[PDB]
Image (cartoon, rainbow over all chains, first blue to last red; front, side, top):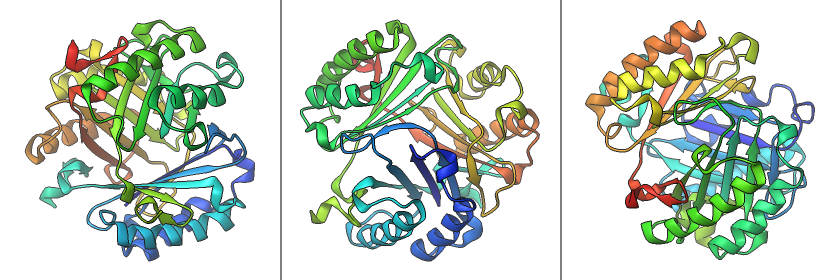
Length: 117
Length: 117
Length: 117
């Protein structure tokens, strides 16, 4: 899966090693191997969330098969909010997540697409 | 709604308070409350737009219900171009927008999804 | 088309002029004019790819008409991997691509949408 986290927290208020811990977390939550989890963190941005510029973060999660339903995204959201709130020292009102299903033909890897792997 | 603005303008050529003004602007344009508008600005990037690396900006807008049609996106585009051209001191040839419909089951908030709120 | 490249390579390990060369490359690969190619490079990010925080890059490609099939995305992936591996001095295991079809009503340009141009 592919995780992208935007935050207006400066890099020095984003705890060291967060991207690796987020790989582990997403493995457990999503039921995917940690060695196929991709994480991108973009700190120090100018953000408003819910109209407010206090510290906040935006998580996008894209994956094949597992982020397409309300009922399991509810579970995923619960777990990622627990992880991120404590990691970033943010309240639940300062984080939002978006979920994006992908298909095999959309993912380029080793010079081909996953359709053929 | 969710706005993401990438620019190769350095942060010190992006006017202070732009993210809050963009919340207000997007409220009026999209017909959504300002306190549910999210803005992310990513300045100082390396960009080419239309093959050219002069100052430019890319706006992405994602929302439920209101960014799914050509006829209303035409109106939205008009208004956001007016706002951004003057805010960033960019010509209309240096900005592009992409619109992305979302569904309730895609948006994680307060540890659940909007399907259940 | 719209290209977005995230990398944990610091800006000073991203070769000068990469965004313009990527315009040219994407023109040839995708069969689109270079003057309608948009490139955004976001360097110096915190990333893990495949669970690993070594140098890596993520490419997103969005376009009308040409990134919707497995068979042609396989070709596109091949060409972009060749370009990026050598440009960024990254191995094929350190790059991934995602492809996103767009429709005319999604693209805001010159204050309208492409549906009407």
